[PDB]
Length: 327
DNA sequence: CCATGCGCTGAC
DNA sequence: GTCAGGCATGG
Ligand SMILES: C[S@@+](CC[C@H](N)C(=O)[O-])C[C@H]1O[C@@H](n2cnc3c(N)ncnc32)[C@H](O)[C@@H]1O
Image (cartoon, rainbow, N blue to C red; front, side, top):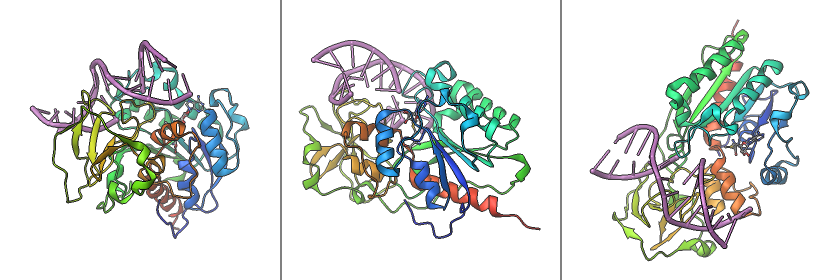
């Protein structure tokens, strides 16, 4: 995460729905906003969130009466993606985990925040022949919000991970915001190798498979792209090895393979997965963030989370637009 | 609860 | 052609 000098969201209150690790909280709080409610139902996520923020989020949002939600200016929601990912069945709204958007809508109808700030997987934009995004747009428009949606790749915003996500920013119509812009990409100057822990700290993560096939020569020049060097097994998910002179593959919550959830990396002649602290870094979490004591739940949590830096640039732009109020 | 071998979708 | 992105069943 990045330093924010000019606190564009000072005086604003936000709610942290589907809170997970609290990435939206770190992002908005860095721009000066104050969290007034969080909701997250997973027991272990609630533990890490409490460890880090001092409060337990409320549980199952589907059972929460929207009248009881504190007044707020910005609603944040990285809602579940398993029903929309190209890695799963794509059942969308037919999946239990696919209809959480309508709980957001329910809350928005009652609370009417200034801004609604959502994230999902890149494929949310293409799912069900575009009808999924269409429904979202139409829902927000009928709630009296504008709808701004763009897929951003983390590697364009200072973070060495190929994580493409759709970001959805909605402004209440009475505010008349006409100048919201998604942040402009810039050159990447940080690579996986720059975020790695000392070899002494990660010996236990080294995997030595006898069926490793090294397909490509290691690179000396750093590059803002993934660079696959070899595979194990049949080369499915978690069976692929990358150069640390490129960027990380997308971290995943439920991913399998021998290099599950992180992917494999060539480091000093050996292949290993990433440490949870390296996953934290690849998601833009500060080293001060406290990781869950279950390494298993930690990998799951970072794989489900958001890239903090990207949310920081967007939040700053939302603040810039809200504060532009000439006579 | 965790591990890991898919399995096939998307997108070039 | 070249690749990257959760589910099932085992323990
Ligand atoms: C994919 S992630 C969000 C990650 C978050 N943006 C971050 O900074 O870590 C979705 C989260 O929604 C939670 N979730 C799913 N269904 C829920 C429900 N019905 N009520 C509350 N939380 C739910 C999941 O446990 C998961 O942590």
